[PDB]
Length: 106
Length: 113
Length: 103
Ligand SMILES: Nc1ncnc2c1ncn2[C@@H]1O[C@@H]2COP(=O)(O)O[C@H]3[C@@H](O)[C@H](n4cnc5c(N)ncnc54)O[C@@H]3COP(=O)(O)O[C@H]2[C@H]1O
Ligand SMILES: Nc1ncnc2c1ncn2[C@@H]1O[C@@H]2COP(=O)(O)O[C@H]3[C@@H](O)[C@H](n4cnc5c(N)ncnc54)O[C@@H]3COP(=O)(O)O[C@H]2[C@H]1O
Ligand SMILES: Nc1ncnc2c1ncn2[C@@H]1O[C@@H]2COP(=O)(O)O[C@H]3[C@@H](O)[C@H](n4cnc5c(N)ncnc54)O[C@@H]3COP(=O)(O)O[C@H]2[C@H]1O
Ligand SMILES: Nc1ncnc2c1ncn2[C@@H]1O[C@@H]2COP(=O)(O)O[C@H]3[C@@H](O)[C@H](n4cnc5c(N)ncnc54)O[C@@H]3COP(=O)(O)O[C@H]2[C@H]1O
Picture 1 (cartoon, each protein chain N blue to C red):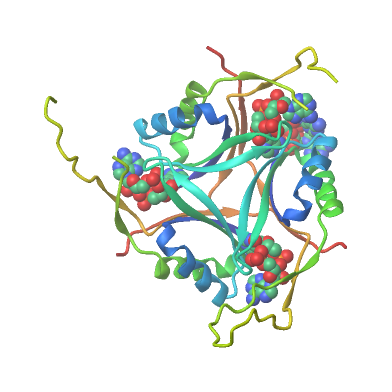
Picture 2 (cartoon, protein in one colour; picture 1 turned 60 degrees about the horizontal axis):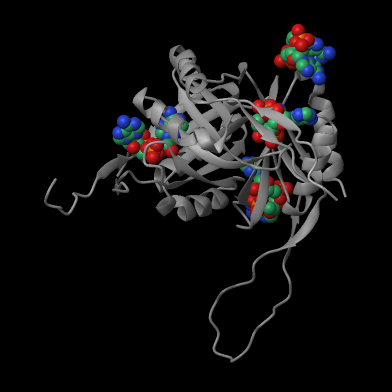
């Protein structure tokens, strides 16, 4: 089993989430911020069997888009130039799981 | 050492945190949402020595209970002038979903000025 | 590749973020809560190449400081402290890494 951490842009979050659900993947969503832009993005945690990892990755790839994102921004004052930063569709880490439990006690 | 990621219901979050502390397990948590119900839940990150893993899992099992949760009803627009309350759709939610991950190395940095 | 989870105090978060960037490391941050003090802190997730793990750990150690924090709850008691570390750090193995760049 593997635990996938996928850091995606907020604009793709809902589409990805719906696609993972359609593909019968469980997932948990975390609100995160990037080290460089210091702005909101989204991290998904997706646990799955080894044999289904490439399927999950394909869903991520197909639902996330690389974009340019704007970064939060003399005698004479000038209007500052926007700062446009390349942001990938997804940064993904696939981690090994030692054991899984689903506790259903009442 | 292992690093446990446990996704639990909000209703159990305070009770689990208290039980971990009483059991001398460290823990960090964060508010998360579920991909299916799109509702708030909590994710715990609990680092533990190998000897203690079964004790940590026991605490999680004991303090995190399965419940039925309502699915948010359809937001589809009607014409009737009303608040419409359809049959509830109840969804099973487990006590905890838990991933135990192997740790390669551990550091606790205590530098001052 | 390895994936570092580093739990640091909020007052070190911006400095750490900047030092990682200066060191050519990527990072993601989670706003978290500690179990014992029940107070806000920051969890960094920093993925890096095997051979650079010790360099990332150095940046973390260098930029995060241990601080004393007071315990809180008919009176304000004689203060009792705990020493919050600069960082609690777990280095985790990564089976695979992907960076999807389709637009
Ligand atoms: N000097 C520099 N240092 C770092 N980034 C710079 C940069 N100059 C430009 N960039 C760009 O800034 C984008 C957003 O970085 P941010 O840290 O906010 O948001 C990141 C961060 O949240 C996460 N991420 C990327 N690398 C990571 C890593 N090694 N560990 C953990 N999270 C990472 O994925 C998000 C998107 O990363 P991506 O590389 O696609 O997109 C990056 C990168 O292309
Ligand atoms: N009873 C047992 N059951 C299963 N495995 C065992 C074990 N005793 C030793 N090991 C294995 O040997 C490693 C070194 O144990 P040690 O006791 O020298 O070094 C231990 C111990 O000195 C320390 N430690 C601190 N507080 C502890 C506590 N409450 N319980 C267990 N270990 C603790 O944490 C160190 C690292 O623990 P970690 O599990 O990463 O690494 C452990 C574990 O992989
Ligand atoms: N078609 C469907 N797809 C997904 N779930 C459906 C479903 N039909 C019913 N369910 C139920 O919805 C419950 C809540 O899922 P949610 O994704 O909001 O909240 C989840 C999610 O936050 C997390 N989780 C579950 N499996 C996951 C995985 N493989 N990876 C990451 N997080 C997971 O644990 C929470 C509770 O999960 P649990 O399985 O006990 O409980 C699930 C499951 O029993
Ligand atoms: N049972 C106990 N008795 C006496 N003193 C205790 C105690 N548990 C914690 N402390 C003290 O309280 C400080 C803050 O812990 P807290 O859980 O709020 O904040 C923690 C928590 O967010 C995280 N952390 C610590 N151990 C962890 C673990 N095993 N798993 C996950 N996160 C951990 O790192 C933060 C800083 O931990 P650090 O150890 O440097 O600093 C700790 C330690 O000085």
